[PDB]
Image (cartoon, rainbow, N blue to C red):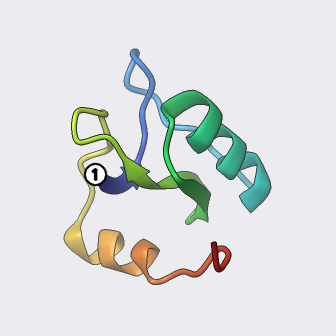
């Protein structure tokens, strides 16, 4: 599995202001483990390798990865 900004079938990402909204999107819509609002877009942890994510800079990627959402 991978982490990244999940996009829908039309290619759009979910814009956000709050983490909880993103965790619902990521888990309920893309079946990921968790998610939070990274740089105003919903970032998902543990997406399926086939899931489409935005083509972003590796620097942004590593930036968004250094987060702890919960210990479970």
Q: Nearer the viewer, residue 41 or 6?
A: 6
Q: Position of residue 45 (x, y in %)?
A: 45, 58
User: In the image, is residue 49 above or below residue 64?
Assistant: above
Residue visible at 23% across and 48% down? 55
Residue visible at 57% across and 56% down? 34
Q: How many marks?
A: 1
Residue visible at 50% across and 56% down? 43
Q: Which residue is mark 1?
A: 1
Residue visible at 71% across and 42% down? 24
Q: Residue furthest front?
A: 72
Q: Position of residue 61 (x, y in %)?
A: 32, 69
Corner quadrant of residue 15? top right
Residue 38 visible: yes
Q: Is residue 57 left or right of residue 53?
A: left
User: In the image, is residue 7 above or below residue 57?
Assistant: above
The local secondary structure at tag 1 comes to loop
Q: Residues within 10 Å of mark 1 (few under 14, many from 20)?
A: few
Q: Position of residue 2 (x, y in %)?
A: 29, 55
Q: Nearer the viewer, residue 17 or 66?
A: 66
Q: Position of residue 51 (x, y in %)?
A: 31, 34
Q: Is residue 72 left or right of residue 54?
A: right
Residue 18 visible: no
Corner quadrant of residue 20? bottom right
User: In the image, is residue 39 above or below residue 14?
Assistant: below
**Where the C terminus falls, by quadrant?**
bottom right
């Amino acid at each position: 599995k991978k982490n990244g900004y999940a996009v829908d079938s039309s290619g759009k990402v979910a814009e956000c202001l709050f983490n909880n909204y993103c965790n619902n999107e990521c888990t309920k819509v893309y079946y990921a483990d968790k998610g939070y609002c990274c740089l105003l877009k919903c970032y998902c942890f543990g997406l399926a390798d086939d899931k489409p994510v935005l083509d972003i800079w590796d620097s942004t990627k590593n930036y968004c990865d250094v987060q702890i959402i919960d210990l479970s």
